[PDB]
Image (cartoon, rainbow, N blue to C red; front, side):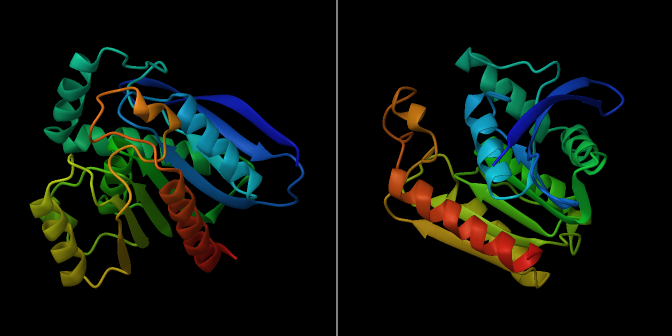
Length: 240
């Protein structure tokens, strides 16, 4: 195709964010938009590449900034404090996620009636927070994402179809948290799907995972391909 990208600067009113929009310049009219939330490191090459791949499918994809000013956490001691600060300030967490969605919708390439969010690890958790906020999203797909309970007011506010792609060997996802979210989605009759991929642990979509913290984080190319296909099948159902 004619894949392009451009820097997008946006804000939640507190923080200045720097994302990246990927799109196919050959596409005719408005196309589905996908927000891409990265791992908790922040907007990195892994997330940019997934936005690029989405543009190759005919979407307009915004790789989102989790931290502000495009900042990329490389000191692993800083990861947990940032994530826990967002766990304890769900309003601020949802505001930065909603700012990314609003910025995506503001782009001339994007069909506001055909929107999705995906996320990797903490980015997937972020995508589910965006769905729980009641944002207008047709589909949400998570990849090796941590899960946590809803807020009470979130009941019935998920409006899209939900697909969780989970590594069955992932030590970082709490089994009680899986039970919790399944229970929320059963109660509210969400159109939800949850796939256990037996081969896979945490970070199974990242070829660069095999560096990090060894056992528990590992690239799994078969699960990467299968889960990407499952995402594409869901998007085709919702968007075609």
